[PDB]
Image (spheres, rainbow, N blue to C red):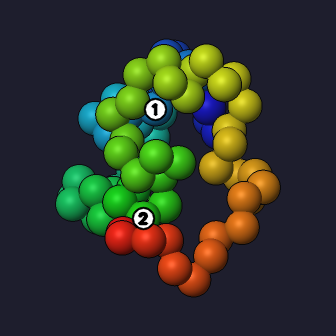
């Protein structure tokens, strides 16, 4: 979605499919694997249609207040 390849370029975001968008980016996949864990919208990356149905990236919008305590984890 940030760049436009094809389905990944505008549609759904996946780890392995994210590569489609940024194919050639990264040295090792583990580096990308590391970043998605905290910084992906759902912290998943390999997501199909959930993100797509929103049409708008809800990650960018920090509408909800991230509290200190979030109950468990």
Q: Position of residue 54 (x, y in %)?
A: 66, 25
Q: Which residue is drawn at 49% across and 71% down?
A: 70
Q: Position of residue 63 (x, y in %)?
A: 78, 55
**41 sits to left or right of 62:** left
Total numbered labels: 2
Name the image quarter holding the C terminus.
bottom left
Towards the viewer: 45 or 73: 73
Residue farthest to the front? Answer: 71
Residue farthest to the bottom? Answer: 68
> Up-down: is 36 above or below 71?
above
Q: In this view of the protein, can residue 15 be seen by the observer?
A: yes
The residue to which callout 2 is attached is: 38
Q: Quadrant of residue 48?
A: top left
Mark 1 vs mark 2, foreground winner is 2
**Sooner in the amino-acid sequence: mark 1 or mark 2:** 1
**71 sits to left or right of 3:** left
* Secondary element type, mark 2: helix
The residue to which callout 1 is attached is: 13
Q: Which residue is drawn at 49% across and 61% down?
A: 39
């Amino acid at each position: 979605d940030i760049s436009e390849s094809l389905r990944q370029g505008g549609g759904k975001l996946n780890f392995d499919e994210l590569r489609q968008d940024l194919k050639g980016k990264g040295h090792t996949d583990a580096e990308i694997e590391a970043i998605f864990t905290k910084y992906d919208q759902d912290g998943d990356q390999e997501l199909t249609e959930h993100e797509h149905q929103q049409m708008r990236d809800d990650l960018e919008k920090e509408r909800e207040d991230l509290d200190l305590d979030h109950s468990s984890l």
